[PDB]
Amino acid sequence: SLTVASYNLRNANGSDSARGDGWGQRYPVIAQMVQYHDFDIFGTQECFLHQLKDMKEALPGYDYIGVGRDDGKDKGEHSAIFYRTDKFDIVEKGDFWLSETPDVPSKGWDAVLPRICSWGHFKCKDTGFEFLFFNLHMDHIGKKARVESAFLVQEKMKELGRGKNLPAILTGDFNVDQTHQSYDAFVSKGVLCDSYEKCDYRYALNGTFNNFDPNSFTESRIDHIFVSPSFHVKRYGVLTDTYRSVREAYEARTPSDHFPVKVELVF
Ligand SMILES: [Mg+2]
């Protein structure tokens, strides 16, 4: 019934631009995808502020929440959440760091960089249905930080209902795949389920990371959408959409180095 997504948009850098995967070329395609596949609300990873402004401008009808992970204002990568303003209101929103001091910009446990989870308390403008939407990007080095981040996020899921026990959706780039201990940490308490396992219908012609290679295949999934067990998950899809650029013959290009994960859930 409603469509949610998780999409790592890939931080802008000159090195991509050089290889022909520049942000300026990708982002217009990303935005088209968001509009065509009708994402109602989606978590993004890796955007600098200027990337968020580009996307906001390409997406009339959408707004976003979430602060920079470096200083909690505008600096650094965001775990930004985009949403259609005609479908959802924000009741409350916030951000916490994946660390022992979640309230402030900080690194956690054995991680090498600061990591942020951003969240919204949303209300469906049509049906009044209310829910929590979380979105994060995990550390690549800190294995303990990833396991602890999972328990931390689940604690936050109990604290943030504003008085209710709200159902939760959690998107993100979890860095390691479904065979890891941090994945099991998310699903082991009965508090969240993997959309991939729970969906009525599953369309998955690939895993989620592609490395800007249009010919890659993996069974690994490092981008997940986890939902409270009370959600009906009607459909799960990996979108393998590609655009083309003139070679130096055209060649296939991925809009990001991940594929988006699209989930349809009943509200
Ligand atoms: Mg990346």
Image (spheres, grey):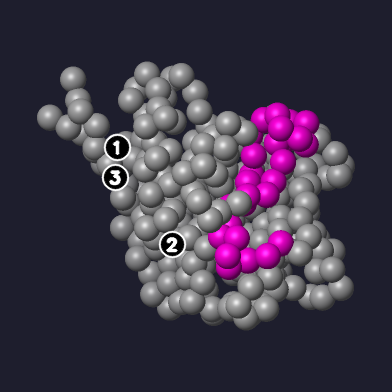
- Mark 2 close to ligand 1, CB under 8 Å: no
Q: Which mark is residue 242?
A: 3
In the rendered view, would you say 107 is above or below 66?
A: above
Say which residue label 2 marks.
38
**Residue 74's spot in the image, x, y percent?**
71, 32
Residue 254 against residue 262 in the figure, above or below: above
- Residues at marks 2 and 1, CA–CA distance in whole angstroms: 21 Å
Magenta stretch encompasses residue 124: no
Looking at the image, residue 19 lies above or below residue 33: above
Image point (19%, 25%), residue name:
247
Q: Residue at x 57, y 39 (%)?
A: 52
Of labels 2 and 1, the one closer to you: 2
Answer with left or right where residue 28 lies relative to residue 246: right
Q: Nearer the viewer, residue 131 or 186?
A: 131
Q: Nearer the viewer, mark 3 or mark 2?
A: 2
C-alpha gap between disc 1 and disc 3 = 6 Å
Is 84 included in the stretch rendered in magenta? yes
Residue position for label 1 = 253
Segment tinted magenta in the rendering: 64-90
Residue 77, x across and y down, in percent: 63, 34
Element under label 2?
A: loop
Question: Which of pointers 1 and 3 lies earlier in the amino acid sequence?
Answer: 3
Quarter of the figure that contains the C terminus: bottom right
- The picture places residue 124, in percent across and down from the top left corner, at 63, 72
